[PDB]
Image (spheres, coloured by chain):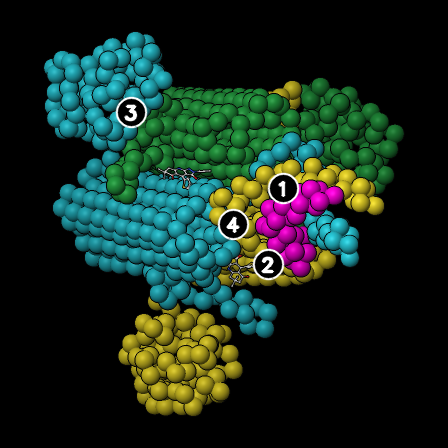
Chain colours: A green, B yellow, C cyan
Amino acid sequence: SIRLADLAQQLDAELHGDGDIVITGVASMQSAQTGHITFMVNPKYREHLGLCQASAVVMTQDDLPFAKSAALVVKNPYLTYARMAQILDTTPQPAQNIAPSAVIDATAKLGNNVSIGANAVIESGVELGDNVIIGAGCFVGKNSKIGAGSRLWANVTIYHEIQIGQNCLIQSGTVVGADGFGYANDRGNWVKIPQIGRVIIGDRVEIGACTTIDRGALDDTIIGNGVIIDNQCQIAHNVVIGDNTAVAGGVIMAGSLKIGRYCMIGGASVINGHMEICDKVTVTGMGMVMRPITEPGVYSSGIPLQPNKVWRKTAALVMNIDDMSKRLKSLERKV
Amino acid sequence: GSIRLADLAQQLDAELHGDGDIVITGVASMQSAQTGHITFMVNPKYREHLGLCQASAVVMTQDDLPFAKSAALVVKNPYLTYARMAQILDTTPQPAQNIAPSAVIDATAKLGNNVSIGANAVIESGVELGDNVIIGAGCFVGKNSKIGAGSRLWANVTIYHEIQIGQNCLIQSGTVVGADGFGYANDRGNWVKIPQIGRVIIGDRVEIGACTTIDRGALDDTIIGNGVIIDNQCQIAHNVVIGDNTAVAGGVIMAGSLKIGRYCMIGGASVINGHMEICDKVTVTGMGMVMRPITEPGVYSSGIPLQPNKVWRKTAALVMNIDDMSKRLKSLERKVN
Amino acid sequence: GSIRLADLAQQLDAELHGDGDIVITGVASMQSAQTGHITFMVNPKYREHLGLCQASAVVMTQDDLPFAKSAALVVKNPYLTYARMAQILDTTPQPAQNIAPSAVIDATAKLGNNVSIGANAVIESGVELGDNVIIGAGCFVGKNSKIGAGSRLWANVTIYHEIQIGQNCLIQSGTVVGADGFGYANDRGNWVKIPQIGRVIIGDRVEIGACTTIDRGALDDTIIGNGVIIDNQCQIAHNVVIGDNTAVAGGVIMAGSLKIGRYCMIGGASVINGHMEICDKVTVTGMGMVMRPITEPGVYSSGIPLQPNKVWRKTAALVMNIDDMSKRLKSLERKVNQQ
Ligand SMILES: CC1(C)CC(=O)c2c(nc3nn(-c4ccccc4)c(O)c3c2-c2cccs2)C1
Ligand SMILES: CC1(C)CC(=O)c2c(nc3nn(-c4ccccc4)c(O)c3c2-c2cccs2)C1
Ligand SMILES: O=C(Nc1cccc(NC(=O)c2ccco2)c1)c1ccc2c(c1)OCCO2
Ligand SMILES: [Mg+2]
Ligand SMILES: [Mg+2]
């Protein structure tokens, strides 16, 4: 719980109302009750602000005349919402102190205030920095290092020789450092190439659930600082992702892809390997990225949904487009 | 457990034609069935084949009866009867039995009657497990989460905090329920995490496949309706709502704040955009690219299917240059007219 | 781990050019190699660059040899030799060693010789682990499952009941083998679960990536042939059959009752529908949308690639209205045919 005046100060927002209002948490506009603070971004909600029952609403200056409650005025309500949600965060920690059922190799090196959940397994040589939290059931493989403040939720798998920076967050089910898909061929028989590279994850990286990041074949798979990666993503061996790039859910990346900084990869996209995407590129959902992207901007692919009867004709015509092309060329020649 | 054919027929509401004393030990495919097995025929083309079936009994329709070469259970719907008898004779073990000494269970957790918790499972403070709930080995159930009576989790399932799961649900291994949604604000190019303080509410009789992820809501909740079935490797983003009885096949990816109606069927590997709605009774075929809202019931499709590589190369190049093709067509139209 | 260069050359069947007494400690890339490392060159464009590589030895061909600036191992196939020497100098640890006191092993489980079981692994009744099997930490192996000699599971792998795995397999973390297929009947509008009492049969020398799922069959079995390699995030549905030596790249989804032949290559993120067959020696390029059986060997492809969004918008609009284009072209043909 926190006073609205204190909250406005920490948020660097201008208060318009009773600063002694006690705020207990954040809520959506439709769900907000007394004691909740909420926010609005779309001006369509201005007009039924008298139905919102929050104790305070974060809004812009143009929204203030429509306010029917105490208001915190700011330039960017969505960013202010992020900050106040962090102040009022109710999320528990993956673990507290070191659980007696955890299995920790005697040669592990633990910083101060390290928490390890029940039945987590820490291999030899592992280094956990100050304030690191390992959730229940995690595995952290030999000689891996996790920087100060980083947190793993339950049932995360970190392989051997992995480096993770400070203040990272990895959600459950994720696997970091599995073998890359590297094989030689000896007369039709696959010959495993041991993957003795690593994964280097920078600082302030957040990784979703059931995402896989393979280790490099010789050199390393590299995730830059401030990268965010959603659920169900596959990052193949020797991929390099530049700082602050965002990767949405279900993206599949092939090996040796290089992605620049400040990129945004839409969900379910497929990016082929041995190529580079430059800085400040946006790929929209389900993009089929076959070629390098050398200029910033927005890129898209795919033929969107149609009613099935219409699709049947669309797909049949598209598959025979070569004949349409030949017929057009013939007609041009005749005319 | 072995059962007498006459007793099995009564439980199935089938007409017995043959020896009710036959002992049935399990269910098998028609090609694999041996003595002691019961099987079923749904395709009348196999009537001439029944003499090659070694099952002790065969479920079939009244129209099939003259072709039987074994004891027969006559029913209106052999496929449904097969589902029912497979449940009666199910050989699937339970994920756990009793409470394993290696399980770690917070003192404040509330266990109902006949709850089983497998080895090395972890149960946090405030958790409530209803009667007959089974938690598989290596599971994690987060703080204050509630799992309704008769629900079962296979091994290595992760339930985060404040999750509500209904009665008689089944969740396969590797699935994660309640992870943080992909919620971030942008501050001059830096991503600022938005804590996801909503929950997930899963209804009754929901089945979730393996390695599926269902994210918790940002403020309000991610909601899975009653009777929903979800296959493997699906991603259900924060604040998605899925209506009762909807089926989601494997590998479907949904964006945040999507609402899917009741009675829908989403084909495997489909991709659905966020902040929009799909109405009731919509079927999206496999690999559907669902970019816009769907406001009328029916079947919808997308995608250009496979061709020989030599042919695809021309197809792809021509489609990508279709604007030029369009211009040439109009130009020729003007010239002819 | 470390080996004299002469002995390494002998085991690789390589021709040594240089000091056989050099001590090699591991493998490294050309750019990263330092004293004690062996590296390899596959691209002759780097011949001029070999003076900058500080590896102690370089694997190369006879045509590269005049350009060497180090001890050299000459072979016909530098890439295959690199695979073999990386195995010889492999630094990858084992998932486990010995039997961990925190593992929970049913009294009726049967273990061969030199079995290792990692911390907090769970082994159900009736399980059989062959000689030299390694079960990583946190794994679950369900009732009556059998794992053949030399096979290894990394941490947090889930094997359901009645699963059969062959010899010298390798399964990466997070993978689930034997979960229920997606089988349901319809009772007047209510889903009715069909118990999935088939199994999964995995052959010998199969490698499966991370967070891959392989469902069990409804009555008969899901079958993975010998020498198959499967990447991360793959979905193999109930009753799929995959022939020997086929490779499945990451993110591939296979619907139920699909049969794939031998020596196939399925590109990443492909979607393969079920109740159909793909013959031997078929290559499906990435993101392929397979809706019909493939009856002839060769390479098959689908998908419209990326364009700038403003260009894509026009392309998508024209394609979605291609029926109108077709009709206009036919009408124009009639006019040109004087009809
Ligand atoms: C629930 C049910 C008993 C019936 C059903 O509707 C269904 C089932 N299994 C499916 N597998 N795949 C699939 C999986 C992977 C790749 C490609 C396709 C579908 O698309 C499936 C569908 C659907 C078809 C159209 C909409 S949902 C079993
Ligand atoms: C098995 C092998 C040694 C050789 C191989 O053929 C192959 C390999 N790795 C791949 N990654 N991806 C991929 C992954 C993610 C997104 C897009 C593509 C492919 O498509 C891959 C392929 C194939 C190409 C064509 C058919 S399979 C390594
Ligand atoms: O693409 C993001 N999500 C997302 C997830 C899953 C599926 C989709 N489907 C589509 O787009 C889609 C379906 C059909 C056509 O298109 C999108 C996305 C990107 C960047 C972000 C972000 C979300 O939130 C944080 C800010 O950065
Ligand atoms: Mg334990
Ligand atoms: Mg996918």
Q: Nearer the viewer, residue C313 or A19?
A: C313
Question: What residue would you read off at disc 1?
Answer: B319
Secondary structure of the residue carrying tag 2 is strand
Measured in 3D between alpha carbons, the distance from the residue under mark 2 to the one under mark 4, in whole angstroms, is 23 Å
Tell me the residue that label 2 is attached to: B265
The answer to whether tags 2 and 4 share a subunit is yes
On the image, numbered disc 4 is attached to which residue? B306
Residue B202, how many percent across, how many down? 56, 53
SS assignment at label 4:
loop
In this view, the mark in front (3 or 2): 2
The numbered mark, 2 or 4, whose residue comes first in the sequence reads 2
Residue tagged by mark 3? A125
Tell me, yes or no, whether the highlighted magenta stretch contains residue A107: no
Residue type at tag 3 = Gly
Magenta residues?
A306-335
Q: Amino acid at mark 4?
A: Leu
Which chain does tag 2 point to?
Answer: B
Q: Residues within 10 Å of mark 3 (few under 14, many from 20)?
A: some
- How many numbered circles does the render carry? 4
Q: Is residue C14 visible?
A: yes
Q: CA distance from mark 1 to mark 3?
A: 55 Å
Q: Residue at x 41, y 87 (%)?
A: B67
Point 31% across, 85% down: residue:
B22
Residue A226 in the image, given as x and y percentages of width and height = 53, 23
Mark 2 or 1, closer to the camera: 1
* Label 4–label 3 contact, CB within 8 A: no
* Ligand 1 contact, mark 2 (Cβ < 8 Å): yes
